[PDB]
Amino acid sequence: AMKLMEVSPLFPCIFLRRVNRFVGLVRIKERIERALITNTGRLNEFMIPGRIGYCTPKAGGKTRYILLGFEDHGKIAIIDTRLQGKAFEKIIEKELLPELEGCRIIKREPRVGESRLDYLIECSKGEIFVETKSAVLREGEYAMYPDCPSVRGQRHIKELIKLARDGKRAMIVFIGALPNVSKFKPYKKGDPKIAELLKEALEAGVEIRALGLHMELSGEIIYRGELGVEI
Ligand SMILES: [Ca+2]
Ligand SMILES: [Ca+2]
């Protein structure tokens, strides 16, 4: 394990209810507060009235707090996809993935086919498109994706497959931002098309990685290393 970054300040809160896919209500001390949710998943196991979450302030505009994660086995599971992405960016910056040494992000959200993928990364010998996905659904030692059907994700995997068949470099990285997981697999029930598409991706040449991450109550974000991938 090693430290990537720190989030400050971090406020414990009580999760009250999800208003819609973008917003939740939480209790912070005396106050009921609107908190941004940046994760399109159901997060049914986390979004339970009474559960302890962790928020950070947001300077402007619509909402003043971001719900970053939830208490999970004494640590914090990171649900916020923006934070997960920032953690990934630190991994790239610090060159902590040997295969991506000497590589850096040159474009964020470039258009690819009918969609956009997270990153275009430039290396010494060429470029690589990298899509990162949240994997915070737990089954024992596994982090899983997704927790419900994702058309957005089906599209992304299709564009990755097409890149690889065109002989371009393509990668999907699952961010297993849960403490105490050592492996990754697709949650077939959540989206059987995605599980089928990930198999097709492997065969086509799309590189698949999964990373273990969590946040400590201190705000420190910890990179545990890679998770064992099953597809
Ligand atoms: Ca994206
Ligand atoms: Ca993404």
Image (spheres, rainbow, N blue to C red):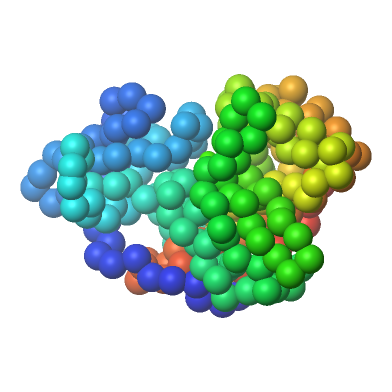
Residue at image position (71%, 56%) is: 127
Instruction: In the displayed orientation, state which residue is furthest to the left.
Output: 30
> Where residue 80 sits in the image (x, y, percent)?
42, 47
Q: Is residue 55 above or below residue 215?
A: above
In the figure, is residue 126 to the left or right of 38?
right
Question: In the figure, residue 23 lies in which quadrant?
Answer: top left
> Where residue 128 sits in the image (x, y, percent)?
71, 53
In the figure, is residue 61 to the left or right of 162?
left
Residue at image position (32%, 46%) is: 67
Residue at image position (38%, 27%) is: 21
> Where residue 153 sits in the image (x, y, percent)?
62, 31
Q: Quadrant of the C terminus?
A: top right
Q: Is residue 88 above or below residue 48?
A: below
Residue at image position (63%, 74%) is: 95
**36, 111: nearer the viewer:** 111
In the figure, is residue 148 to the left or right of 170?
left
Q: Is residue 165 visible?
A: yes
